[PDB]
Image (spheres, grey):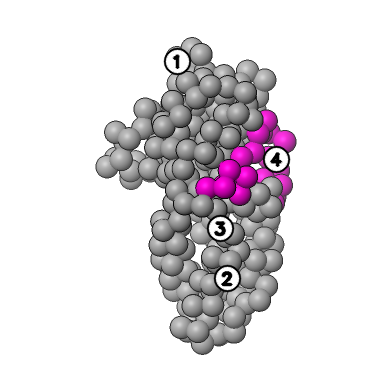
Amino acid sequence: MIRAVFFDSPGTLNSVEGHAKMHLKIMEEVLGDYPLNPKTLLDEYNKLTREAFSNYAGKPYRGLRDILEEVMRKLAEKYGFKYPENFWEISLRMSQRYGELYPEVVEVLKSLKGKYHVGMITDSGTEQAMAFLDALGIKDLFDSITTSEEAGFFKPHPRIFELALKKAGVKGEEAVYVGDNPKDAGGSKNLGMTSILLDRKGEKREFWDKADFIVSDLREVIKIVDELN
């Protein structure tokens, strides 16, 4: 019997278009009048952050601020613009204004509340995770918020999923995990959770077999849970 539904944050909640627009604005403010195409800076920032997040997957927690600040130091020395001492603050200010939930998020979270334990699991630090939820107005829609900083390890390490389950007071077999990255269908299945992969654009077909179910819209989750029960 499914008693809890956990969501991968921010990946299944924040729209890719809002993320891209928000981050483009971050780099525009970082650069100002500097003769560097902000989109090029962003592309290279994404290359470096993607590599970093890949290297730390499953490993002991390390602060994301230090990671991103070192990335921006490498980009500043590479391109010659002034290193943004306020990069973290710029990011928070731009996520508040330009962060955008997928259209169905609130509906889905509301439909699960009461019926099931609605949880969030994220590799973000706790402060960042709370600021993210606060900016998008959905902090109180979750019964639990579990972070890598609390567990001590990044996904797909089992401990972050184990902690989420213990917060909810449910067994792995009683929980679903809805995940964006094909870190998700892995650490959660190690705890006996049912793994749902969110693939909105159908661009992850190579990794579908790693998940128990594949959805393109979070509104499909409630249907899957109801069918399981």
- Element class at badge 4: helix
**If you read the primary sequence from the N terminus, does the residue marked by circle 3 or circle 1 appear first?**
3
> Which amino acid, mark 2?
Glu
Q: Write down the residue under mark 3.
A: 62
As drawn, the label of residue 139 is 4
Q: Give the structural element (helix, strand or loop) at label 1.
A: helix
Q: Is residue 226 left or right of residue 87?
A: left
Q: Earlier in the sequence, mark 2 or mark 3?
A: 3
Query: To which residue does mark 2 refer?
Result: 69
The residue wearing badge 1 is 228
Residue 28 picture location, percent across and down: 58, 73
Q: Are marks 3 and 1 in contact (CB under 8 Å)?
A: no
Query: 191 or 15, which is in the foreground?
Result: 191
Is residue 229 one of those drawn in magenta? no
Residue 222 visible at all = no
Q: Secondary structure at mark 3?
A: loop
Binning the other alpha carbons within 10 Å of mark 2 as few (below 14), some (14 to 19) or many (20 upward) gives some
Q: Distance from label 1 to label 2 (Cα)?
A: 44 Å
Q: Which residues are magenta?
A: 131-153
Which dot, 4 or 3, sits closer to the camera? 3
- Amino acid type of the residue tagged 3 in the rendering: Arg
Give percent across and percent down for residue 188.
45, 33
Q: Residues within 10 Å of mark 4 (few under 14, many from 20)?
A: some
Report, in whole angstroms, how far the alpha carbon at label 2 lies from the one at label 3. Answer: 13 Å
- What whole-number distance in Å separates the C-alpha atoms at marks 1 and 4? 27 Å
